[PDB]
Amino acid sequence: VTLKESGPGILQPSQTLSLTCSFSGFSLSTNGMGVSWIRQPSGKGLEWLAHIYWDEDKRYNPSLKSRLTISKDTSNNQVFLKITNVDTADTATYYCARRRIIYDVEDYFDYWGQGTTLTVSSAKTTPPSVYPLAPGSAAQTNSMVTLGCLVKGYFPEPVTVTWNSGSLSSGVHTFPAVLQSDLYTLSSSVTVPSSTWPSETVTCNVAHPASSTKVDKKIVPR
Amino acid sequence: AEFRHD
Amino acid sequence: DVLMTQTPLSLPVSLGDQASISCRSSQNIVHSNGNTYLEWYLQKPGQSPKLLIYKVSNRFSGVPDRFSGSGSGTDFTLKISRVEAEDLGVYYCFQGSHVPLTFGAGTKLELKRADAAPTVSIFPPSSEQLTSGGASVVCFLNNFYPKDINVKWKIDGSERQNGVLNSWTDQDSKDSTYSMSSTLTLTKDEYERHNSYTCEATHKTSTSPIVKSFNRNE
C-alpha cells in the first residue's frame, strides 16, 4: 500500500490549486475505505482538510469548507483536492492519508504519502545577492578561523551553498532559510585551521536552480 | 457534529 | 473545535531513558458510538507522520510494546520506556471523533547531552553589500547545548530590537549540539551613524553573557 501526491508547487494569491493523490495497495470501492487530505506548514502542526468515503460521502474542515472540493477516481485509484482562491496561508506540505471506518480496529491513518510542497507568493523569481563574510577588520590570530557567507533576498527556494566546490565539507553550518518580506535569505559558516586560510583560498558557491544562476565568492581578508 | 465512523 | 495541547513541547532524553508525553483535549472526545478516537503519530525530519497508537491504548501492528498509551475522557499519555535513536522525532496526538479532526502542536523528542558553550563569531558587512545600499551584520553562535539560548544586538551600548533575523539548526546527529545564526539588517546610512557593534549571548553555560564586538572605523 502506497500513496503519492502530485500537483503544482508555487501558485499566486487567488489562483486555484488542484492536487492529485495517486494510491495503490487498496481500492476506494472497498466497503469502509476512504482518503483524506492533511497539510502542514513549515515547522508547524498538521491541519486536516477534507475526507472522502467509498459511498461518495464527503466531510470538510468547516473553517475552509467553501474553498475546498474533494473528489475521487475510483477506477483510476486517485483522489483529488481543489482549493479555490489560495493565499500565502495555504503555504504548506500537503499529505493524503488513508483511513477506513466501520471497524474501529482499522479506523486510523495508517498510510501517508511522501507529501508534496506548495508556496503561495506573488514575489517574482529572484536571484540571490551573495556576500563574503571575512573576519573582524583586524582580529587576533588565532588557532581556528571562522568564515561566513550571506545569501540574501531570493525566490523561490531552494539554493545550494557549497564550500570550495564541495571539497570543504567539514566545519560547515548552513542555516534554514527565512523570509524578509517576499524574499528568502540564509547564511553559511565554515571553520578551518588558521594555517589553512588565508594562505589557501576558501570560496562560497551559491547555486539557485530556479533562477538559473551560479555565483562564486572568494573570502578575501579584511 | 461528529465525524462519521459507520 | 477540540484543541489538543501537548506537554512538554521539547523533551530531552538520554538513549535508554523513559519518556512521557501528556496530551489533553479542550473537551471530551468519546464519540457517540462509544469509541474514543485518540491516536499518537510520530514524524521524523523529512518523513511523513506514522501511526503508533490508536483508540488510546492500542499499538498499531509493527510497534514495539516499549510504546504504550493511556488515558480517558480528556486526559492522555504516551510512555516510551527505554528510548531508542529511531524513536527520536516529533510526536503528535490526534482526536478523530469531532469535526474538524485535530492534532497537537507536537512534541520534539530530542537527545540529552553535556552542556557546551557556543563559539560566537561576529561579521561586519561586506564592502560588496555596502557599495550597494544595505548593511547586514551577521553573527554565528555554533555548537552549544542546551538548545535554549538568547541573543541581544547592541549598537553603541544600546539594545536594538528591530531588524534581527534568526535561524537555528536542528539537533546535530554526530555531536548532539545546536547552532544558530542571528542577522541585524540595516541601511548603509544607519550603519554609518554608529561605531561599535555588539553581539550578545546569554546561555546556561555561563552567568556572564558571551560577547563579540567590533568598531566600524577600524
Image (cartoon, coloured by chain):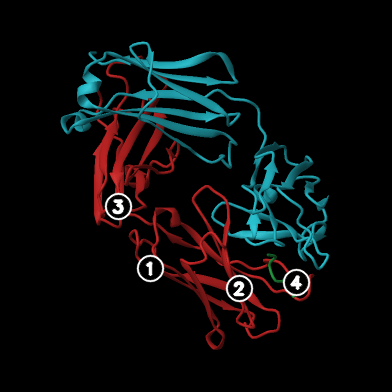
Chain colours: A red, B green, C cyan
* Residue A82 % position (x, y): 45, 71
Q: Give the mark nearer the N terminus: 2 vs 3.
A: 2
Residue under label 1, please give it: A16
Marked residue chain, label 3 = A
Q: Compute the Cα span from label 4 to label 3.
A: 45 Å
Residue tagged 3: A208
Residue shown at 25% from the left, 39% from the top: A217
- Residue at mark 1 to residue at mark 4: CA–CA distance: 34 Å
Q: Cα distance, mark 2 to mark 4?
A: 13 Å
Foreground mark, 1 or 2?
Answer: 1
Mark 1 or mark 2: whose residue is earlier in sequence: 1
Q: Position of residue A99 (x, y in %)?
A: 67, 71
Query: Which type of secondary structure does the marked residue at label 4 adopt?
Result: loop
Q: What residue type is disc 4 on?
A: Glu
Foreground: disc 4 or disc 3: 4
Q: Chain of mark 2?
A: A
Provide the residue designation for mark 4: A106
What amino acid is found at the position of numbered circle 2 in the picture? Answer: Val
User: What residue does disc 2 label?
Assistant: A35
Going by the numbered disc 3, the residue's amino acid type is His
